[PDB]
Amino acid sequence: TPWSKSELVRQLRDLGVRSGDMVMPHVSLRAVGPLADGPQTLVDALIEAVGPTGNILAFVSWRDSPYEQTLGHDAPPAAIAQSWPAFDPDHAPAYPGFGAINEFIRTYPGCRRTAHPDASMAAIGPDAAWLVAPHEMGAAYGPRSPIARFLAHAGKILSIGAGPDAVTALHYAEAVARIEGKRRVTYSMPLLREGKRVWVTTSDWDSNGILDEYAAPDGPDAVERIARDYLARTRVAQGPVGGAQSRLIDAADIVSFGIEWLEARHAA
Ligand SMILES: CN[C@@H]1[C@@H](O)[C@@H](O[C@@H]2[C@@H](O)[C@H](O[C@H]3OC(CN)=CC[C@H]3N)[C@@H](NC(C)=O)C[C@H]2N)OC[C@]1(C)O
Ligand SMILES: [Mg+2]
Image (cartoon, rainbow, N blue to C red):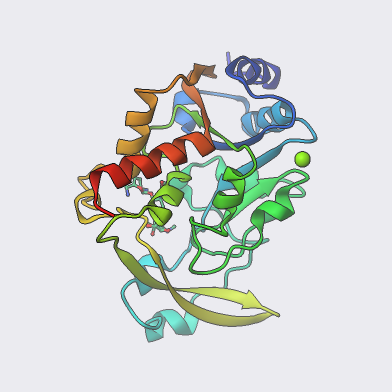
């Protein structure tokens, strides 16, 4: 029979989620299996698990981000520029390919949303406003991003049946890693500034592979290779959440591991 909220809360407590914790979930709902009231039951359990003084941060992005449509141009192509919707943080659906749970997180009453349309983060809790801003274009996952502040706030990464490729915080490791040959990308996003639609073009680190050898689509990335090597070497709390094998990862520790991992393999 489908998992109940209190059952999930018990599993999260066993895993090491505490009242006051700041948690970043990565969830495969197919692994979890049927839920009493659908995905909201797990959203509710995470909110109950972290308590009223805890916080949830999620990488939700945007269903309609014009990423591929502007990549590699110094300006949005005319047909894109002339009609694309402005990013409206309180009305933009999450990108479905990063987990169906993100649309439930981001529509939760009181949730905050970062202003980076492609890297958009969602946060719930007393620290949500501090988490989500600033989030400038050009600072998607590195210093000054919500990922950076999460790492400075004892964040835990909660992987719920998700693979080692689904660790967005490791992009911070890619951003600051002192290695040669790091790829950069240029794209354009449409923000709303004082009700006016404004196209902004910026450059950031390539989040589809920080080095040439990691950016092949067929095709494991650096995140997957770092996270798997880390889990092979580190004691990490493991156990079920629903039907999904889950991990509770110290975010500061795995990112610090990732910096050492990349810099040891590539010259400074
Ligand atoms: C919303 N628009 C998107 C645009 O933001 C960008 O998304 C990337 C995203 O691909 C990438 O996840 C890939 O990581 C890898 C291999 N590299 C395995 C899984 C891949 N999905 C994210 N990193 C994670 C999840 O750690 C960063 C994100 N910035 O490119 C595609 C896009 C759909 O257009
Ligand atoms: Mg607090």
